[PDB]
Image (cartoon, rainbow, N blue to C red; front, side):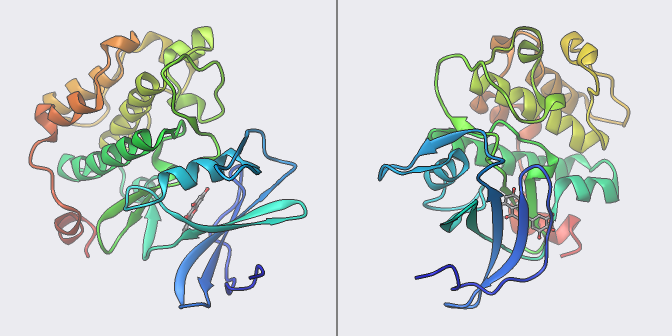
Length: 274
Ligand SMILES: O=c1cc(-c2cc(O)c(O)c(O)c2)oc2cc(O)cc(O)c12
């Protein structure tokens, strides 16, 4: 087989997650993203079904791929002396929500709803596979600008979903819930909704609501943009200080504000100039 069944191209990014490149599988000219991750820089490791030692990101990806959307799928992977190449899909054209928001500030609610709903369905998929993303935010959400579809990325901070309490966290602090900041404890589903909460605000206000820990723990939300009474209610519910006062995924999707969402294609036709 060998590593060379792909034709490497530019650098689409780099940072904490690793270093992502623009490849094109030679086998059938299909666009792909190539993520190198040094062995030495990995923290969390798991073991694949077949019984071999890989980074948790690979285990999670594998569980969450299989079937369609919501998530960038992992087509293949390789092990090198001091790293791990991950071959992932590269749909196009594409922009991550952080960049998108940075460019156009806060979004309209009709657009935030399409995006938030799509995000919601992708998190549901992740939980069904037994994966908890743990780092849901605007930087880890790609937007296929042509088809109007969002896809999840970067599981390097995730963990196997479980019903017991989590006493470890390595994602984004400002998206982490109050219960983590105060006792270093949290339950996946509860904590997920909280980050989803921060993300909804972020979309409709053009920036995150909490910057400091003193603001997370307090849990009072100030709105800087014109935002509908209904959208404010859902953001505040998703950010209930008490984890069990936060909504379920079902509750979030049956909320008045999430009715009559636009379909991916419609969404691009109206808001992405596509
Ligand atoms: O598939 C992509 C794709 C990109 C990507 C692609 C672009 O075309 C681009 O402009 C980016 O900023 C990121 O970034 C990442 C980061 C990760 O940590 C995991 C991933 O699977 C990906």
